[PDB]
Each structure stands twice: as C-alpha cells, then as structure tokens.
Amino acid sequence: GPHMATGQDRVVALVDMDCFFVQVEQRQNPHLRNKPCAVVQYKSWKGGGIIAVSYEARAFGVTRSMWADDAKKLCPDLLLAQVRESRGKANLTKYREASVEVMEIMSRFAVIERASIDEAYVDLTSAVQERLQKLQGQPISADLLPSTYIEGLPQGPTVQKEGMRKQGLFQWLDSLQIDNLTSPDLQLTVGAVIVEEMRAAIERETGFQCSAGISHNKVLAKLACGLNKPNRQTLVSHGSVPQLFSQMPIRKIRSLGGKLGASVIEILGIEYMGELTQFTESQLQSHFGEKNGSWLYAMCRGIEHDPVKPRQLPKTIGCSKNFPGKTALATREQVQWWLLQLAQELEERLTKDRNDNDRVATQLVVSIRVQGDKRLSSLRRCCALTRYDAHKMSHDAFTVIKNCNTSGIQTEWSPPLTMLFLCATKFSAS
DNA sequence: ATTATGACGCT
DNA sequence: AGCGTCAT
Ligand SMILES: Nc1nc2c(ncn2[C@H]2C[C@H](O)[C@@H](COP(=O)(O)NP(=O)(O)OP(=O)(O)O)O2)c(=O)[nH]1
Ligand SMILES: [Mn+2]
Ligand SMILES: [Mn+2]
C-alpha cells in the first residue's frame, strides 16, 4: 500500500512533429499548404516511395511505404514533393537542418533527448517545480491549456470535437488539488502548461506544428502524443492507465510491435496490455527474460524508469543506399564508385558536424547486404576513422569488405551487392 | 523493388 | 566486435 511506489516521480513529455517532411516542404512551397500532399524518394520505380503524408492525404488512405503511383489511385489530386538527390542517392540534409531548428527551440525549456529526426523527450520535473513555486497555489485556468486533451475524460454525466475536449478539461481541472505542490496530477497539469508554451514557440519560430504527450515516463508520453494528432497535446495521468490499457493491443506499446510482442500474445494467450497485470513478475521473467519481464510487469501498471538522456545530437552519422533487383552492384568498379559516393556524402556531413558540435568520429562501420539474403545487413565490419577524407574512407571500406567477393574474376562482384552502408561512430570531443 | 536511417540489446 | 530487433 503506502510503500508501493507508483512511478509518478517525474513529468516527461514527448514532442513529435506532425507529418514532418511534408511540413518542411509546405513551408518552402506555399502551393502545397493545406493540400493532400506526400513526400517521396526517387521517381522512376512506381512513382517513388512515400515516406511522409499530410493529414488531408491520409483521409484518402495514403500511407507511408506506399508507391506514389498507387497513392495516386486513391487520391488523384495528391501533390508530391521529392527528396533531393545528390551523388546518385537520396539526401536528407534539408530535414536534418529543420530538425536542428526545432531541437534548439525545445532545448530552451529543458534538456532534451533527441529520439529521432522529428521528436524529442523532455524531463519537465524541475521546470514544473519552478512554475508551481511561481503559481503560489493559484489554480490553473483552462485558457492556459487551449490544445490539451485529458485522456479518459469526460466521463459519466457534447456533439462537437472541441466541445468534448473542453468538457474533459473542465472535469480534470475541477478535480485538481492545487494546494498540494507534490500532487502528481497537478504536476502533470503544469507540465502540460509548459508544453503548450513550447509548442507555441516551435510554431511561432519555425512555422511547424507538432503534437505532444505528457505523462510520468517516456512510454506513456509517446503513446499519449499519438492519441490526438495532429496539432494537439494529450495528458495521460497515472489514474487513466487501467482503462486505457484494458483495450490497448499489446503491439501499440513502443518495443512490443515485433517478435517479442507476438510472443507475449501467443505464450500468455492475451490480447491487451491490461491483461498483463494478472501475472507475477517472476512469471513474466520466466517467459521473456529478466529484463523484459521486469519491464513488462511495471509497464502494464503505467510504470517505467528509462531516463530522458541528455542528448540533443545523434550518436552516429550514416549514409546508406539499396540496390534492388537488377540494379545490384556486380562489378568492382561499381562497388568502388558507390562507396565513394556514400563516403563523399559522409565526409560532408562529418565535416559540418565537427564544425557545429566540437567532436570527431573515430570508427567507421561498413555494412553490406548480398543478393538472396533477406536480412537487413549481410555483414558488418569496423575500421579506424582517422581522417575526414572520402577517398580514404571509401578505400578503407573496400578493404574491409573485399573478402566478400566470391568471384574468382578480379573485375566481377559475386554475388551482387544490394546495399551499401557507411556509418561514423564513437565520437570524441575535439 | 520500400528506403534511409538511427537506437540499442545480446553474446 | 559482429549480429539481431525495433522502429519508421
Ligand atoms: N528516409 C526515411 N524517412 C522516413 C521513414 N519513415 C519516416 N521517415 C521520415 C519522414 C517523416 O516525416 C519523419 C518523422 O517520422 P514520423 O514521426 O514517424 N512521421 P510524421 O512526422 O511524417 O507524421 P506524424 O504526424 O504521424 O508523426 O521521418 C523512412 O522509412 N525512411
Ligand atoms: Mn512526426
Ligand atoms: Mn516521429
């Protein structure tokens, strides 16, 4: 009872940009704004592959991973923006630079954990304590939460979406105990006020809209963020978890959408996250390992301890290109030319990284996939990265992979290569 | 012939 | 170190 820690110590937010690459292109090209729009890479094969979709286009069924030609069958007026091509490959520099814009704004409010090109976690615990001090016990006005949903409300004792949002927010605020500076629900509410301010700053200073989740840990904050996109934020309280998880398919939790989540479902004969509560910690550890078992035992109760890491920058910088079907690399000249193309992009990104961030990569990882292998990587080899020079890096990558070529002929490459991947790792302060 | 990444756990 | 998983 009283000693049963409830994982309510922290206030954690997850901010995720809405249809991010689409918004970057819509900012640049006003003709694309407020339209069914998608971003594609390449064009020749089936119109290119869609990687981002505006909410207007999603209403027609357009999704990521869809070929543009098929998307056009669902949405004939779909507008398309193509990712830049440089050195024969997709070049995502524009979106990385836009990401840096957003991360630098978020960092004004708290130390952030960059989790992807378009999202970051925020530990707002200390900022919340400060704002609570400033409030001096003053209640929180609904006017300070103009885009916030409270998950699970309204309940009990109404036709429009905004009206439902305001009803739930009123029920939440009316039940708040604001004389207690240690009430977790109050702390979450102040966190949501701060996140409204952060999201307002992002939109004012970049033009980009985003959604967010506010809860007591990273997994619940990420889930919350998804609940009401686009352009809204959602508060998931500790008390909302039993109802939320009672119908939540296990795969919707981050980390359980693959083989492990399938094994939870099959071994235990359950469907929903809430059903996990009936098992002991030891039972879950016996099926899924000590670490996964403890994580599942806590997570189905709304509890997770993974910290928001103080990391605004990516840990690795990588360049990769697939060579599908008849485009697979089958000569030594081809392999060297594309290694050089990847290495040149890598050199340019690394040199800019060193200038901006006062650090140097020290290890080069070379990954390839060979024809007939379904795995992502057929082989990974590391070597030393001592100079930011594309010719040296491509020569070294060739040296570490060249023993892959089973062809006796010096010129041919067999079996052909369907992917090259260069990734710079192990950064040191320079 | 989804693609280009990036994080992280395991042994 | 190299591989596998999850993600998207
Ligand atoms: N190259 C590449 N980029 C991708 C891929 N998948 C996503 N991206 C890029 C394009 C995406 O814009 C961006 C962010 O990914 P999300 O947050 O998962 N999706 P979004 O922000 O579009 O919509 P929502 O409002 O639902 O969050 O990452 C991929 O497979 N390949
Ligand atoms: Mn997003
Ligand atoms: Mn995202």
Image (cartoon, coloured by chain):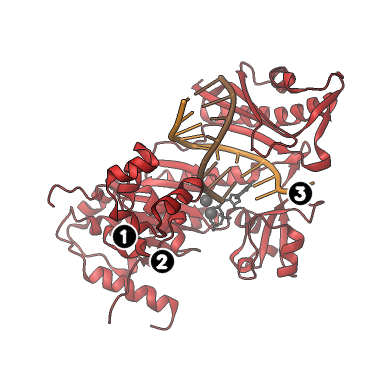
Chain colours: A red, B orange, C brown
Residue A164 in sight in this render? yes
A300 vs A392, nearest the viewer = A300
Q: Earlier in the sequence, mark 3 or mark 2?
A: 3
Tell me where residue A20 sits by quadrant.
Answer: bottom right
Tell me where residue A246 sits by quadrant.
Answer: bottom left
Is A80 situated above or below A6?
below
Determine which residue is flagged by label 1: A241
Q: Earlier in the sequence, mark 1 or mark 3?
A: 3
Determine which residue is flagged by label 3: A42
Q: CA distance from mark 1 to mark 2?
A: 21 Å
> In the image, what residue type sits under mark 1?
Val
Q: Earlier in the sequence, mark 1 or mark 2?
A: 2
**Chain of the residue on which disc 3 is drawn:** A
Residue A307 in sight in this render? no
> In the image, what residue type sits under mark 2?
Ser
Q: Residue at x 64, y 65 (%)?
A: A33
Q: Residue at x 82, y 39 (%)?
A: A327
Q: Residue at x 66, y 30 (%)?
A: A346
**Chain of the residue on which disc 2 is drawn:** A
Residue A147 numbered tag: 2
